[PDB]
Length: 240
Image 1 (cartoon, rainbow, N blue to C red):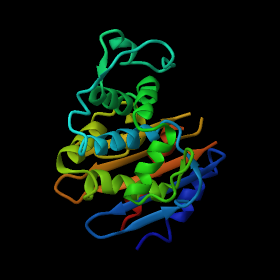
Image 2: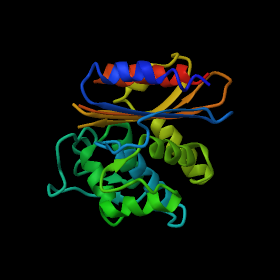
Image 3: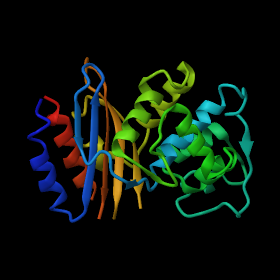
């Protein structure tokens, strides 16, 4: 149990960038929890878009045909960061494609649309309460709560086999988070992550070591990409 001697280098890291750093990790094959400020309030930034597609995936189970439903655009929902939204403007875009755009590219326009067809911002709160997350609020959560929530959706039995593995394949394809937890792992390890761009940043991921049990973790900061990567290495090695 190296969880007592990891608090020293973590405090070294968070005192070299100014603000605070919250980190939680969990071992599926044992249960080792490397915790450090993992139960503090941390801004979610653009990381809610990972759970937004998860709520959308849960809707499509008892609402067949939901993901192939397309949406047309105008301009009352067009906002900055529109990599795939404005690229497929008048051609429309399905809900499934709308979710793959908001996760794998942090599309701020596609996230606004999926929020509407969920009941608004509180619609995402209802989904997180439905699985067990009691720390989710309007957007704050603890690095531990982000870990258990992501654990249930991608690994645990919370999303059905089609929608669960679809969620995993949606995180595996995320592009904005290579300079963070993706860089802090052996390249041969499969990784699926979601980032948060606000300065203050964060990243939660699931790591698949070659022939070993997978690991869920969350690194949250507030004042920075190499800082999250470094904090990831600390939590990964900290699991004795």
